[PDB]
């Protein structure tokens, strides 16, 4: 099972982008998303989608991201421009058979995430969207396989 | 060459999602993006990226999307969840040797997008971000090689 941990969500600014992260996570085969800042309106939006389009994807908000990432029972993946290329490590991640937590949304020089993660993974050295980074990570993990709701 | 056509840009509502679309278009190997509503902030942002990171990508805004799509000289692709499975059609599109214009919308897209397109293309039947739809479209078009492209 893959869980996305989305940090740096600002309820009063980032509803759209965080929504886009959650829908991408769901569509491309993650089972859950955890969001740092509590956002009941986001929960209601996403839970609405899940109701309307099916399946058991989970959203929780108001999470302590360092604790969730630190104590996750499985592989901790940090999506970041400061990371090695996904292709270098994706097979080993996939072949591990473990649950995976993928951290999206880190900023600054992301020390606390780098202190915790098992893998720090980039797609390109060009500026990209975290939404597109998450899509590519999930696509590579699931090897381009399609999903059934 | 791939040109992205981004519609339903509403610059006084949000510029982040369209900026993310443009950054994705550029990084994933499109040559150009055309955006329906004029947005000089967007133009300058993306031109700033080109200045610092290289390559020859172009952005224009304030475009009549129906006219651009209808009269584009090449294959008109519309990315939509209500389209055909991408893997059914991506090979024909790639092997045509034609230029491609890829329409990416937001909220509801006008029915004309579906009627004009040569191919209405679904990366998934589930609601997703236009950013991730575009990423996967380009990724499949370029068969995973686009991150080797030089800027």
Image (cartoon, coloured by chain):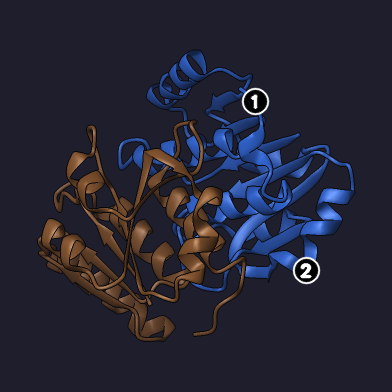
Chain colours: A brown, B blue
Q: Nearer the viewer, residue A109 or A114?
A: A114
Q: Residue A12: where, in percent of width, then height?
A: 14, 49
Q: Residue furthest top?
A: B51
Q: Nearer the viewer, residue B131 or A8?
A: A8
Question: How many numbered discs sit on the rendered protein?
Answer: 2
Displayed quadrant of residue B118: bottom right
Identity of the residue drawn at 59% across and 33% down: B33
User: Is tag 2's residue or tag 1's residue first in the polypeptide sequence?
Assistant: 2
Q: Which residue is mark 2?
A: B88
Q: Residue B134: where, in percent of width, then height?
A: 57, 50
> Numbered disc 1: what chain?
B
* Secondary structure type for disc 1: loop
Above or below residue B27? Residue A146 is below
Q: Residue A50: where, in percent of width, then height?
A: 35, 80
* Secondary structure type for disc 2: helix
Identity of the residue drawn at 36% across and 58% down: A21
> Numbered disc 2: what chain?
B
Indicate which disc residue B150 carries: 1
Q: Is residue B1 visible?
A: yes
On screen, residue B130 versus residue B32, left or right, reads left
**Which one is closest to the eye, mark 2 or mark 1?**
1
Q: Is residue B9 visible?
A: no
On-image quarter of the N terminus of chain A? bottom left
Crowdedness near tag 1: few (<14), some (14–19) or many (≥20) residues, C-alpha within 10 Å: few
On screen, residue B34 versus residue B37, left or right, reads right
Above or below residue B129? Residue A73 is below
Q: CA distance from mark 2 to mark 1?
A: 29 Å
Residues at marks 2 and 1 touching, judged by CB atoms closer than 8 Å? no
């Amino acid at each position: 099972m893959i869980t996305v941990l989305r940090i740096n969500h600002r309820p009063y600014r980032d509803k759209r982008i965080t929504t886009h992260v959650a829908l991408t996570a769901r569509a491309f085969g993650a089972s859950a998303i955890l969001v740092d800042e509590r956002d009941e309106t986001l929960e209601n939006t996403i839970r609405g989608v899940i109701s309307n389009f099916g399946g058991s994807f989970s959203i929780k908000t108001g999470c302590n991201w360092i604790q969730e990432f630190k104590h996750f029972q499985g592989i901790r993946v940090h999506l970041t421009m400061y990371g090695r290329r996904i292709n270098d490590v994706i097979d080993e991640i996939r072949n591990s058979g473990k649950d995976v937590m993928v951290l999206v949304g880190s900023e600054k020089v992301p020390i606390e995430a780098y202190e915790i993660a098992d893998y720090n993974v980039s797609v390109t050295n060009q500026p990209i969207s975290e939404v597109s980074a998450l899509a590519i990570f999930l696509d590579r993990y699931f090897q381009g396989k399609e999903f059934e709701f």
